[PDB]
Length: 41
Length: 324
Length: 131
Length: 55
Image (cartoon, rainbow over all chains, first blue to last red; front, side, top):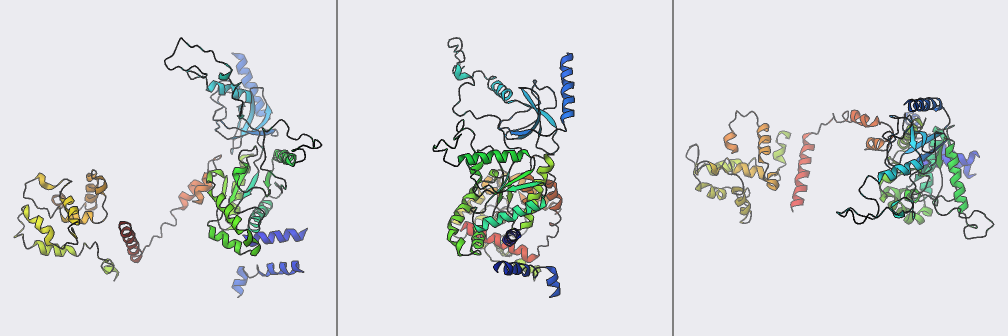
């Protein structure tokens, strides 16, 4: 719940440095929790 | 009699023609009464069978004794609602069937103290409070989130933000969400005729921000008049008891956490900044949990964000289908 | 193993399956044959002849035993010299665990009917023992 | 319990979720295996709690 809320907050803040790497980190943190990554590994 | 049948037919045709007119406003009752059993209804057998604290939508006008309206129930038809003065009359009829209403008791004392009913035996007295049977509540009940901690701290802000985003996305094009920066807990109706009518009085309330609160009250009223769903993001709500005696009567939504350990673990997961306020966060959490379930309107106790999302979505879908 | 699991998990404090053999061994010293019914005096000593753990641990639990023989309907309605092995060991095995007729003491017929419907087909040999 | 609240929250419309749990409650109560180890464990728990209560 908290992470979904945080990514929504970040998206609405950026849509209108730290921001770029934070967006990349969130995208990475979501590409490792999908069934595709599970089956590939 | 031909006149009564003629007025019956006229009222029925008027209802049939006005079934498809824009809704004017809405009210809420606080008394137990049925609109079908009365003989003064212009249409017999098609009254409203309501109870205490029910919501009515009024579209057109009938007279000083009755109005036309529908219920917020799903599939509710058009009936007639007794007027404020008519409800006062029927309430006086409620307290007249008894043996006595005034000061002279009937405890085996008849024929000596007639004691004609004075002003104390009528509705003229008892004006110290004078709670009105009818109140003009907003047409659409505002949706407000409370819990699981103080608004303005990370856990609560995100826990509410996620639900706000879900509501905006699922109901896109049919819902309006605005943040209410101003205070809201002082939504009073019977303080005075006009506390602080002008800002140049330089009085205690003229220089205050109460007028902002009232202005936000009419803003919420007119936005609920629009018939579209409204969700409030005011950061001054931490218990429904602070907004239960007002006129808005918003839909209280509770996003509770199963146990205190989970909440404080969650708080620890944020950092030291929330560790500083963890004490007050726990205090408000336990105080809000001690609030009983009947105080709230809906509950969100599921630990999964999705399940709570579809729960709230189903409740609001039921509300939308009920008021159309 | 599972077929004897209830025996392998005894924790003997309310042991009932194994003490019936001991009771039979003790009772066989008095009764010469079936004889239908036996006298009254033997059972008072019999309550002590058997293993004390079931019926009276010490002198104090004997009071509970004194409560079992009295305070409720007893076969005394028939001949004075009547067996109580149909009413003593039944009473002990009925009150030792799942005891509900003690707090009320009035709804005996319902419990008797439940017991009978649980033993509905025994060829009606117990009716005499239930009394 | 959720299905009880999903019907307790709605009084303005005849709730169909009340029957939803009734028809969906007996689908998961069919797999009551409860092997003899589990039954003996339950009986032992009852005996131990009763002994603690009597003290």
